[PDB]
Image 1 (cartoon, one colour):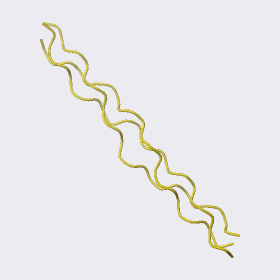
Image 2 (tube, rainbow over the protein chains, first blue to last red):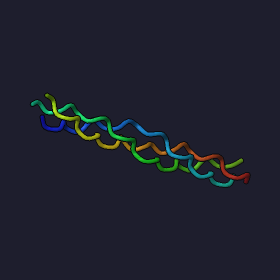
Image 3 (cartoon, rainbow over the protein chains, first blue to last red):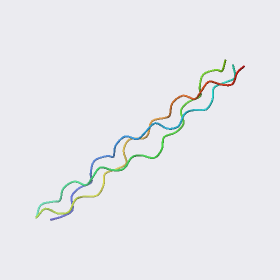
Length: 25
Length: 26
Length: 27
C-alpha cells in the first residue's frame, strides 16, 4: 500500500531564557 | 493495499526568545 | 498489507517567551 499521511504536530517546547535585567532603581 | 498509518509526531519548535525586561531595581 | 508509516508531522507550536528578567541594579 501507499505511504501514510503526515503525522500530527510536535509537542510544546519549553519557555525561552529569562529576560534582561530591569531598569536601575 | 491500504494507505499506511500516519507518521509520528513532529519535533519541538526551536528555543524560545528571551522574556521581557525585569522590574526596577531597589 | 498497509503501506509504510507517513512522515513526521510538523514542528510543534512556538516555544513561549521566557520569564521576566531579574530586578535591575540598585538605584
